Image (spheres, coloured by chain):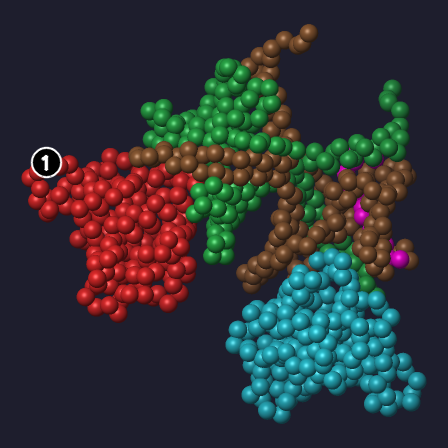
Chain colours: A cyan, B brown, C green, D red
């Protein structure tokens, strides 16, 4: 009987990264994968806490209106959802994009020096490899610059599902069936991590 | 004095009843095997337990249709046939939300209430999870089939609501 | 006219008896899940079957000690722990020699005889194998526990003899 | 409910192949593996027909005494055991030895152009690889010169468990635990073959 926070990274005025021609953004793909994953977890008897359920950002219009302020308030509000939830786990869904288009693959991250989160990340990365792309040999990497993963007291991981910078992967990431495959991989990773202890 | 000797059929039917109600048995089996040469002897231990098997398969939300979870023993099978994936996981130990036999059977501390044609059964969920606090089952007082089940958070809000439709048993 | 209304405890105990004797059930489950946002709805089918689990583990001939065969469902587990090997095989469908429930329970054409303190039960083994022709079970007429079982070839020679020792059940 | 013929190749006056120094022979190793395999099968509810249970050969002393005649009569008698048994399967256990000591590995054979026997052989060869030696990449080979495999009407295979010509393998083959491992591999191969259909 677990309670899991799923965070579709971005929303509202904040797209994420973009494709070369700026047709495709992180917002919508993150939300799509997160809602697929929500369905997997809830139909298995877990309770899901969402930071966002739709295309919105966690800020109020006070017309101070600094885009950097809007972004910062969004992050603070997501942090409070983590703090006040009494959840067992936090999973953030993003995508990556670099200037070099040759990079591809799903990549998981965990907050530096948190062992439980490293184990969870490894479970999810193994499932992302086995289910989505056996070609992918990426290893889990620590981070210390993701605010939402710092100092949470629960296992916390970020998943960058693929690169919008890569044309083949971008085309895959806009596909509802590929999105479901990724959600399946993440869900299985969570389930293995939870079955050990 | 003592009863009369049982006939063939009385002893046989007693035996049928005894082995039918059996939920566990265990014995030592000394086996002699005789091929075309010397016999050979073996000793085995035979263990029998009657065990529960639950299958939950999702039909409605199209994304999940045909996905399933199967609870067998120490094992759990999680199946996504859309990509022909089967994952086996260990069972640590209600097995799922909607599982009512063996928690509403094996009575403990429990609130029982007879209200508006329903047997209402309430238990606390151990672990003091804010979200999975109390489990309430509504049973039809005439059919004794379960109608509804609610998992309530610590504030009494249903977080999970199971409505049972088309209930049949043997 | 009609009987008096059942009290709380009478309905509850009826429910306990009904779900305890259940060997199969099936239903449609409409589940509402309410997180911190909109509820979401799911439809599952729940299936329950109570299933047999048999384990045979070899103890006596030292070479075989600790080797085992486990019959669960559609599955069979064959284990040699001396090399930490576990092999999973499919179950096609008596599951082993010594298996007596559900063949001597589910009566068919069958010879029943009451001889010298034993219920003797004889069935033919289908397939007309020269070597596995007839299955004979000796049951203690007082305990109704099985004492002995013989697989006889077509000439009446026991090819397998199982002697049951230390039989306990629940 | 299967009945299986196990044939420990050789016996009595007929050793098999021999080690370089002629200390070690096929007779005793074949019998040892065959009796381990007999125990595996019988404890699983199969019935075993043995051609030999001890160190003897299937001939009678008529003092005509041609060693070639003794060998031929041995083979005829084993053939009659196959013919008259109404068994489901025939397994012969031998060993190999060549002038070149570099050769090693368990090798299975099946009678040419018998499909069922080829399937059974493949099952056993796969288990011999997985259980005994993952190094071994030998494939099942047809034969048409093994009398006991010709025209049997039941699935029939010969297993040459290793090479006495190879010093490391010979030392392994005299070890009771290695013999049990081989019996386990053969037993599992049989069981897989029977589980398919
Ligand atoms: Zn992002
Ligand atoms: Zn030979």
At x 49%, y 27%, the residue is C148
Residue D19, horizontal then vertical, whole percent: 23, 60
Q: Quadrant of residue D73?
A: top left
State which quadrant residue D140 falls in.
bottom left
Residue displayed at 57% across by 59% down = B86
Q: Is residue B86 visible?
A: yes
Position above or below: D113 against D72: below
Where does the image place residue A49, in percent across and percent down from the top left?
A: 80, 67
Give the percent coordinates (x, y) of residue A191. 67, 63
Q: Nearer the viewer, residue A17 or B108?
A: B108
- Which residue is the site of mark 1? D62
Where's residue A45, x and y in %?
74, 57
Residue with the most extreme bottom position: A99
- Count of picture labels: 1
Q: Residue at x 41, y 48 (%)?
A: D191
Q: Is residue C137 magenta?
A: no
Residue ID at (81%, 63%): C35
Position above or below: B118 against B4: below
Magenta residue check for B150: yes
Please state the extent of the stretch shown in magenta in the rendering. Answer: B141-154
Q: Confirm if mark 1 falls within 8 A of ligand 2.
A: no
């Amino acid at each position: 009987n677990k309670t899991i926070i799923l965070d579709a990274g971005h929303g509202g005025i904040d797209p994420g990264a973009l494709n070369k021609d700026k047709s495709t953004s992180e917002k919508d793909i993150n939300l799509a994968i997160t809602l697929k994953l929500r369905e997997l977890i809830e139909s298995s008897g877990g309770l899901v806490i969402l930071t966002r359920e739709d295309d919105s950002s966690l800020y109020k219009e006070e017309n101070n209106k600094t885009t950097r302020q809007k972004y910062n308030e969004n992050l603070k509000n997501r942090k409070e959802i983590i703090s006040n939830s009494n959840a067992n786990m936090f999973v953030s869904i993003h995508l990556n994009a670099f200037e070099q288009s040759k990079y591809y693959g799903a990549q998981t991250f965990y907050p530096k020096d948190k062992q439980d989160s490293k184990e969870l990340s490894k479970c999810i990365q193994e499932e992302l490899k086995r289910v989505v792309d056996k070609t992918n040999n990426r290893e889990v990497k620590p981070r210390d610059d993701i605010y939402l993963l710092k100092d949470n007291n629960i296992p916390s991981v970020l998943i960058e599902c693929g690169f919008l910078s890569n044309e083949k992967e971008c085309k895959l990431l806009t596909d509802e069936t590929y999105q479901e495959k990724i959600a399946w991989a993440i869900y299985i990773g969570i389930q293995k991590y939870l079955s050990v202890d | 004095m003592q009863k009369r000797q049982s006939t063939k059929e009385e002893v046989y039917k007693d035996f049928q009843k005894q082995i039918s109600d059996m939920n566990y048995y265990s014995c030592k089996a000394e086996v002699e095997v005789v091929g075309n040469k010397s016999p050979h002897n073996y000793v085995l231990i035979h263990t029998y337990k009657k065990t529960d098997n639950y299958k939950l398969e999702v039909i409605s939300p199209k994304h999940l249709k045909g996905k399933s979870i199967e609870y067998q023993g120490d094992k759990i099978l999680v199946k996504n046939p859309k990509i022909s994936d089967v994952v086996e996981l260990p069972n640590t130990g209600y097995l799922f939300v909607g599982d009512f036999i063996k928690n509403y059977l094996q009575n403990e501390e429990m609130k029982v209430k007879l209200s508006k044609g329903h047997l209402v059964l309430e238990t606390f969920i151990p672990g003091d999870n804010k979200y999975f606090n109390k489990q309430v089952l509504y049973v039809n007082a005439d059919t004794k089939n379960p109608e509804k089940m609610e998992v309530l958070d610590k504030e009494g809000v249903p977080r999970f609501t199971v409505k049972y439709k088309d209930f049949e048993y043997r």
